[PDB]
Image (cartoon, rainbow over all chains, first blue to last red; front, side, top):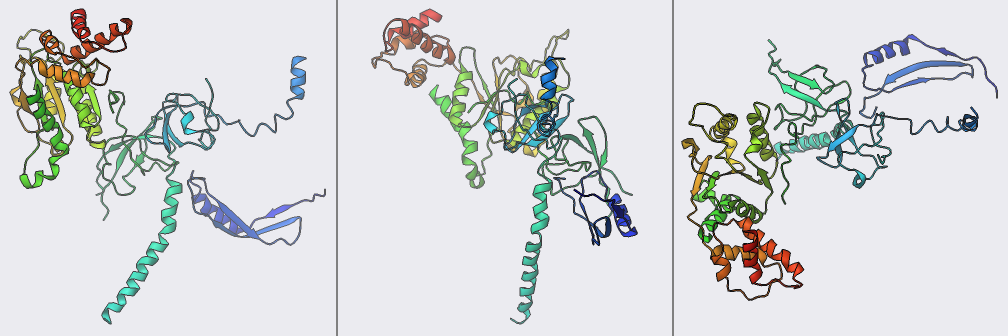
Length: 58
Length: 83
Length: 351
């Protein structure tokens, strides 16, 4: 039962990829994934970000 | 307030019972069936919708021009109703 | 065969294609499975100046007009101003077009699952479903429109309805006043829709009655209520003339009175067969009555003379009504088997 202060690190990579995902942000429901490495508990870093093919199920 | 007391005390599990049954498409009524997988349904807003029958409702329990409860999300029919 | 050794690589590329189309052919099923609503499609030809101009006009059930070209897979019966088309979210594209007709109601009219003349009639209705394979060598073109008429009291309606059971196909029922309504311009829509159902469905049987009353050209110049079925018939003949699809399922017409006749009804696609009824005989009616009553239990002694003689200017439905009436009092007579005198008793009863 322990909780610390976490802060999400965002680079230009994931940002621009989410901008392209913004162009992909058509009303059709879309999927995406984020990758990175955890050095410790209270910090989180994301680096590799890509998109996913659309589907009719959503 | 006293009759609503025990009910207010019984309103605790309603939060955990809120997840199902909550979906309402406002009971759109059907018309006819050309084929079994796909049915044509006409809402009271005069907008025709099409959705496949779920596994929770038997195709033999479907009557022509019958009002049944229908999901507004999955668009399928979870449960029918007598009236 | 050294030059033909390069074919193997080609076949490998082809089977590789067949292997790599699995996924893109797989996504079709999950994507196109559930169209969320139904929209009206109207075809409009545009011009781009390949870069060929293509477009369409859409009408949503929510009354919101959008823009979109003509797309989707290979189309055949499509491009027509129909309804019930597949559509995805925000895409407003066209995937599966199925025609259920317009204002369905007219279409669900009904669901149905004298020897020398009835022989010719039976042969006439049987031959288009039979001799088509022999029509190539013989070059015999089957008649389409068939005019069945005669003096009142014949009972030709239930006779043709009885022949419809012999055709084994689906039978429909359309009357004269059914073509007359309060609205206007119903003729074209009715004809086009009926021909649409005739195009989509199996070679069923279509029979219309009372074409004489609705086909009256009213020599008297003062007034009358219905001019509509006149031009409806004219348009019907037009589509039965200038159209190649007319080789499809036939439409049978019948007139009660010969007072009104259109000289333009003569054609292969139009009315061809003309048979006048010269006071139909008795024994034949007794025969068909025997065929109808063979199912019921009756004492097998009948002179047939009395029942043949007592029938004058009576329909077939009236003869069946005589049989039914004979079955009515046979229940309260206490007898479990129908007798001979019950027939004539019924005749003198209802008539």
